[PDB]
Image (spheres, rainbow, N blue to C red):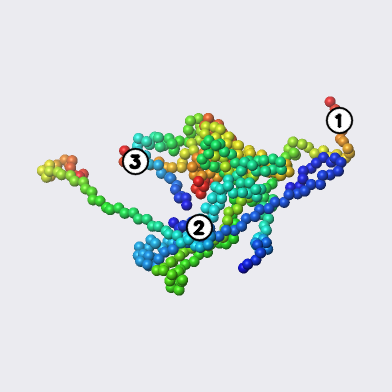
Amino acid sequence: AIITPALISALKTSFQKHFQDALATAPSTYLQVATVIPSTTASNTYGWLG
Amino acid sequence: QFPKLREWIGQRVIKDMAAQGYQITNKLFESTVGVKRTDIEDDNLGVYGPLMQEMGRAAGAHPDELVFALLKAGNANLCYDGQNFFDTDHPVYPNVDGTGTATTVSNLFAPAADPGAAWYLLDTSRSLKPLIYQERMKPSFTSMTKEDDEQVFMADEYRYGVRSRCNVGFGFWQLAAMSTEELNQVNFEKVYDAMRNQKADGGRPLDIRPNLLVVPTTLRSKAKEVVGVQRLANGADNPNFELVQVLDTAWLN
Amino acid sequence: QFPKLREWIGQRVIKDMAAQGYQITNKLFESTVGVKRTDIEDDNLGVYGPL
Amino acid sequence: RPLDIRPNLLVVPTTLRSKAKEVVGVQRLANGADNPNFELVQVLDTAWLN
């Protein structure tokens, strides 16, 4: 019956992870407005003919 | 959340994470009704012993009362961060955010918008113990011999209402919900866009998708014109038609 | 209806229930028509008869 | 606890029959708008009223 309130009153709990990943983040969208051009050096120079 | 990407200048700034916790304890509940032996045993009409089924349906209806009372009192009870679930001062890293709008002029009934799509819903409930009942219908009972009789019928239940993120929910805008304009569209699209414009700890959008609109029976007509009418008063479209599904409940206000 | 649930603090609070009653008594009505024997018993065209 | 009440019948005399049908019975209000009160309550027209 009688017991310190720092052992039983502390350990009478059940940890659950329902709250984990409850919310999300905005989906990727840069694909719809940009192309992917891989690079192999410090910079990329572009040139086109008129 | 992991710290945001930074431009590499000099050394690195080693940052820290932020773990959060929510604690909530079970509560004890009971409803008990006492009658007399002579009353029931002299009841030849038979309109005095639906007590069993009345008590059963009361036990069944208790969770509705708990959850919707918590929804009502969301402006008073606190969420995990430290403020009220519906408060104007929800804290972000340096910033302050509000999820409750008032007018100080006309604030009568509050509609609620709940993005229930997420894995964790709003105003959750916890069920530690199912319902259990007991009677006093034998001679050997202490109550049966305490007076003429005390034929008590009671319920035992361990429950308590819970809540969740107090930024995914916007459930107090008592300004108005229906008019020719600026109440039908403004104060509803305002809630929708404010919830879709939330910012997480770190500087990332929350990606909120409001889908449920909860209103009392008195504001159902306003809610239905806001969502559920295809045309407009001038013959045009309602841009908010079929935007969110509305639910009418009588457990609030 | 059964009383609502109450938080457990110390002792069970024995509650009371109620029953209601309604009553109404029947009433007697009438409609009466008076006709003359010679008026209808001499009716040869059948004007009277749907009475 | 809340009471479940579901109105389903509107009772009017003959003189108010046109008003009742206009309130419930017409799908377009003024400019092609949609009547929010269309097909929710069935109107009853009886001459035993006023």
Q: Residue furthest top?
A: A50
Query: Mark 2 — on which chain does it sit?
Result: C
User: In the rendered view, does B125 fall on the left or right side of D20?
Assistant: right
- Badge 2 marks a residue whose secondary structure is loop
Amino acid residing under circle 1: Gly
Q: Residues within 10 Å of mark 2 (few under 14, many from 20)?
A: many
Q: Amino acid at mark 3?
A: Thr
Residue B228 seen in the figure: no
Residue C5: mark: 2
List x then y, in percent, for residue C38: 10, 43
Q: Amino acid at mark 2?
A: Leu
Q: Which residue is mark 1?
A: A47
Q: Chain of mark 1?
A: A
Mark 2 and mark 1 in contact? Answer it, CB < 8 Å: no
Q: Residue at x 65, y 48 (%)?
A: B82
Instruction: Name the foreground residue: B224 vs C23.
Output: C23
Nearest to the observer: residue B9 or residue B247: B9
Gap in Å between the C-alphas at discs 3 and 1? 86 Å
